[PDB]
Length: 119
Image 1 (cartoon, one colour):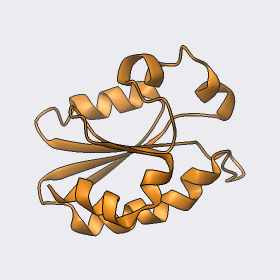
Image 2: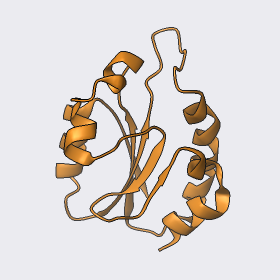
Image 3: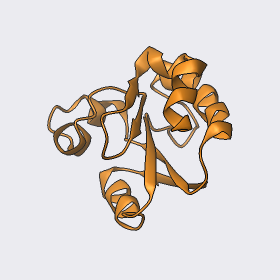
Image 4: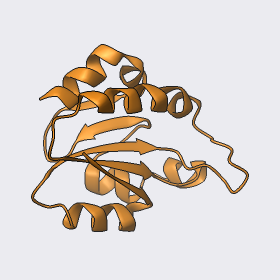
């Protein structure tokens, strides 16, 4: 699998367009500041679980690690992630273009994560 790391909606949209013909999995998480501090506790706890699940991904897939921005931006009800992708909580693990998605505490359960990356 090939990983792509992006920050913000613009970069995300760009990344998906360049892989329009591949199975895409996207992980939406809070951004870390210059100091490396994360405002989303659940995101910090879930990342290692999601990445461990990557060992189960089927060949030929794409994984997009997406930092959505700072807390004030995420809280804005009009931000692009909420309005365009219907992502209303972080962390969120989504199989792009499909209904399969895991949210918040679901991202901490290895079984659920594995089942999403499997097929």
